[PDB]
Structures are given as C-alpha cells and as structure tokens.
Length: 48
Length: 144
Image (cartoon, rainbow over all chains, first blue to last red):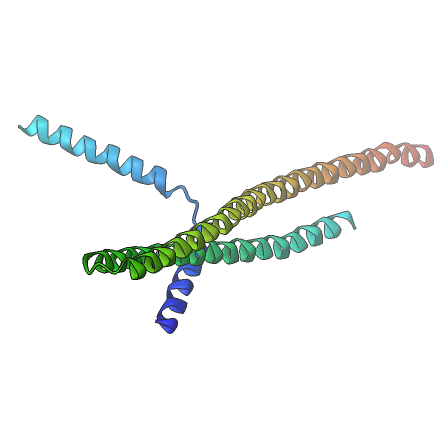
C-alpha cells in the first residue's frame, strides 16, 4: 500500500503535469465535429 | 547591435517560459497528489464509519466512539488537504495565466521589431540613393 499510494501520488502529479499545459483549440474542433454529425443526421432525415 | 540584443532577450525569455512550464507541471502534480490524498482519506473515513456500525451492531459503544474519533480525524485531515489543494489550484491557474501573457508579449515584441527593422533598412537605402543620385552628373557635366 505504501508503494502503491506513492504511484497514485505520481499519477496525480502526472495528471496535473498533462492537464496544466493542455489548454487547446481541439475543444472547438469537437464542437465542429458535433455540427458535422448534425449535418449527417439531417442528410439521414432527407434520405428518410 | 539592437537586432542582436533583442534576439538574445527573446532567447532568454524562452528559458524563463520553459521554467514557467516546469512550475506549471510541478503545481499540476502537487494538486493531483493532494486530491489523491484527500480522496483516499475520505474512503478510510467511510471504512471507520462502517467499523462503528459493526461495533454498534455488537453493542460496543466504546469501540463505536473510538471508530467515530478516527472518522473525525480523517475528515479533518481531508479538509486540511482540500485547503492546501485550494492553494495549489490558484497557483496553477496564476502560473498558467502568467505563461499565456508572457508568450503573447514575446510574440508581439518580436514581430513589431522585425517590421520596424525592415522599414528602417528601406529608409536608409532610400536616403543613400538620394545622396548618390543627387551628387552625380552635375560634376561630370561641369568637368566636360
């Protein structure tokens, strides 16, 4: 449990270290992907 | 040369912003590790509450009050780690906002200097052409 909890603290430090830099455009790209998915559902409604 | 001086200043700023990325990555690890600590302390507080429920089922009020005192100690310790976490969260965001501001300032400074250098070189070249074209031909015609 001592070794495992030290690896949990290493995973919290790793999760901070990834999360603290990773502010990106990609969230707005996922909003464009949801808009494109909405166009494919409108094309499916047109086919129906 | 001011061009070499401002390029070196921008290079020094790359070292400083890389140290600020290291400070963000450190602070990210501290907030994640202190979250992990309070998360496991609150899970142990549930285990000690269940130890009190078993003691109360057996009629051992002495063991139940001791187990509840362990629950109290663990939830107070998790509140101490949540208080420290709040300091790591505000520091993490402060370093992040300072990094975004520093990167923007470097980019603007370098591009404004680059266009000013190009305009200054054209201005001196135009002035040099006025000095060479302005003197010639007149002394040639007078000498002839």
